[PDB]
Length: 269
Image (cartoon, rainbow, N blue to C red):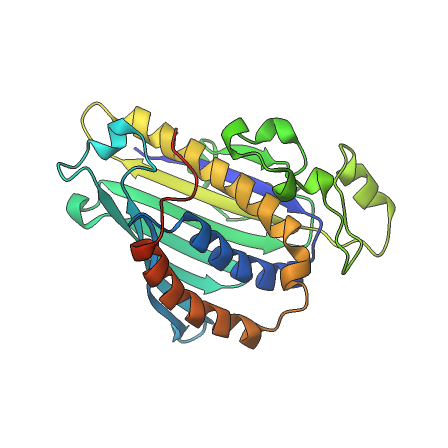
């Protein structure tokens, strides 16, 4: 037994800018959560060959102490957690698997994403078998709706409902932002269908932890995409190679941030 939810993020950007946007934003975000000995450590970032499928592979470590609640922290005597994240990014499809050495296969967060040029209208894009599909909650994340942000997390500068791109004129995103999007030609949009699979088989904490992760993943996909957008002007002119170099700089910066910096980031639920 295992808990499955698909997050549907509609965005006012093209499947092709998104490829770059995301990649940039993963790094910015990584940096905003690293410090105090917590956050992101990159170990591997390189192209791969499965033979027929080509794309980029990463192996990261997420370091967690205080940014998670007491009851998670307490799963380990050292009061501290490393979770390993191996990802195969074959944009427009990505498969991400988070595991924990100390736990065999009783623990798993897996994210499977398909980026598609529509408005989230596709049921079961991931072609799951029908019984399993029956148990999937589909959740829409609206990057405009401020009710969807945790108060602690809100920032007017990370708010799409308040941002206008100077480089492209997109924004800011009013309550109808969607309906409007449908009304005009020179308006791209995609949906990220992120299927998240959570497994945590541990006596008496399974439902509790499973649900906590889904709520934390959802918080992330919400701030992240808010930020992706409010960050348009920073990545909208960027090349893949402009990105791979960022990635390199960022591997070292994170290694320096996590050591020399205060705790920053999201603070946990």
